[PDB]
Image (spheres, coloured by chain):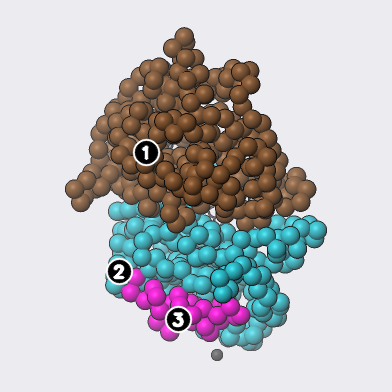
Chain colours: A cyan, B brown
Amino acid sequence: AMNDIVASTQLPNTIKTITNDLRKLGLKKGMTVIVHSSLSSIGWISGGAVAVVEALMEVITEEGTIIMPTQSSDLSDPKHWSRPPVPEEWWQIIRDNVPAFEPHITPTRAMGKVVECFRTYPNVVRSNHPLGSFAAWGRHAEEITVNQSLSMSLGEESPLRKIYDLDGYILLIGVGYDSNTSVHLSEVRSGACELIKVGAPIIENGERVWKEFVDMDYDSDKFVEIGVEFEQKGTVTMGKIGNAKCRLMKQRDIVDFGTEWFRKK
Amino acid sequence: MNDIVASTQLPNTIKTITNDLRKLGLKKGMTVIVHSSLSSIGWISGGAVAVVEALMEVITEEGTIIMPTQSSDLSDPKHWSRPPVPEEWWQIIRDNVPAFEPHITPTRAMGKVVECFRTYPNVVRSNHPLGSFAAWGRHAEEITVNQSLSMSLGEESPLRKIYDLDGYILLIGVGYDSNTSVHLSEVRSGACELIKVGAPIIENGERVWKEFVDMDYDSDKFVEIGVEFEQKGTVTMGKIGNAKCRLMKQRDIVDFGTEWFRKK
Ligand SMILES: O=c1cc[nH]c(=O)[nH]1
Ligand SMILES: O=c1cc[nH]c(=O)[nH]1
Ligand SMILES: [Cl-]
Ligand SMILES: [Cl-]
Ligand SMILES: [Cl-]
């Protein structure tokens, strides 16, 4: 309900107030940052998702880099679907008919309106993976998004590793660690999960192909627990953007912690 | 979503949606303004993309597809009721809401099909900050250029261009209260009054809140008009999956509507 969102807000959030809140929390010009958001968590915003994207770009600038996950699990093999599952009798029709990934076109699923706004901005570029893409904007946009591997999509050949190499930051706006994509790189590095056979529809040599490949069975339901232990160290900056509880942290910090956590089990 | 899946027999796909459109009477070269509810169709392999691609496959670049891309999010808040907001906020809103930019501004209440449509390559969008439309195909640029600020859905609008082209209206799983073309009947009959409105635009480089006048567009009579119109028998009914659909000529409904409003 928009009703509850308006009832819960004292004054409008605007590009200007958001920009203020972001700077207060520690975002600054030139920073490399991957962002995860819930728009409704902030309270009512004048301009909605556009105001958030504009505020982020204002603070970070073209001399910095904004990254967001642009996952499209709508295109994944339906045998592994539980959110919701679909009947087994549909599975093969989906493989034969789900449209192939095209980075300018394919909508995201479960990423949020901010992401949908962001990925269609001018000068925003998207990585090539049919399930596990990211979108970036700014100084290191091209470098972060190019040459993502089909297999091991969130691993050492992915945008996550490039953010790591850039000593980047993670901003969570009113969401928890189950939305912290970067912790998948901890899974890869720790060998935390099983490999499984997955599939996705791609344009390959100029035609739709249902492509089979192997990826880790990524599982964000362990992340919340990792997050609680991580924040005992006291290296996460916490604060508000409007009504939302937000967290700013160094990506290497949580990735390294997650890797050591999985290894010790 | 579990509800959508359970009420679907086999998946809807590009191939099945194209087939349903063609039985419904859509064909190559047509000019059509489309209004839709994605969930109404049942479960779709590829969601909004599948619908958009199906419409394009049938109509082709020789025809033209139009959709409303309204962004009422940017309007003057004094007139809001869905929901309304405290008066204290109104002026703050006017001074801070971001300018309309056709390649960026999201729609409000148009549906995922429109949000997907408006981002497709070769889809062009008109420049009105509240009542823009998006178009694709032969007459896309014709239909979307030179929309007046004032009288946004009037004689200088895409609705009239569709009218001049003798185009069609396709309603997918939605009723006549989503039938944007009937606002032209409102304009023609003088069925609403004028009001003071505003919008944020890019003017000579900068953001500017621009105050203009427009019709108090009210769709509350549209359902009633639609019921009466369909006794004429000039509306094709059909199914796209689970959704009950309607295909009709735009000049038909617009003229009926104009006549309907003038007799009160
Ligand atoms: O319907 C869907 C699509 C993707 N993933 C799911 O779990 N369900
Ligand atoms: O919040 C809003 C925005 C536009 N229109 C409304 O009625 N309410
Ligand atoms: Cl940095
Ligand atoms: Cl290591
Ligand atoms: Cl919160």
* Residue plotted at (75% across, 45% down): B7
Please tell me whether mark 1 or mark 2 is closer to you in this view: 1
Q: Are marks 1 and 3 on the same chain?
A: no
Q: CA distance from mark 1 to mark 2?
A: 29 Å
Whether residues under marks 1 and 2 lie with C-beta atoms below 8 angstroms apart, the answer is no
Q: Are marks 2 and 3 on the same chain?
A: yes
- Residue B168 picture location, percent across and down: 52, 34
> Is B141 one of the magenta-colored residues?
no
Q: Quadrant of ligand 4?
A: bottom right
Query: Residue A42: in sight, yes or no?
Result: no
Q: Which residues are magenta?
A: A138-166
Counting the numbered discs, the total is 3
Q: Which residue is mark 2?
A: A62
Query: Residue A239: in sight, yes or no?
Result: yes
Residue B130 tag number:
1
Binning the other alpha carbons within 10 Å of mark 3 as few (below 14), some (14 to 19) or many (20 upward) gives some
Residue A162 tag number:
3
Q: Amino acid at mark 2?
A: Glu
Residue at the outermost left position = B204
Camera-side residue of A200 and A31:
A200
Secondary structure under the numbered disc 1 in the rendered image: loop
* Residue plotted at (44% across, 61% down): A119
Would you place residue A172 above or below residue A254 in this image?
A: above
Q: CA distance from mark 1 to mark 3?
A: 40 Å
Q: CA distance from mark 2 to mark 3?
A: 18 Å
- Residue B8 picture location, percent across and down: 75, 47
Quadrant in the picture for residue A138: bottom left
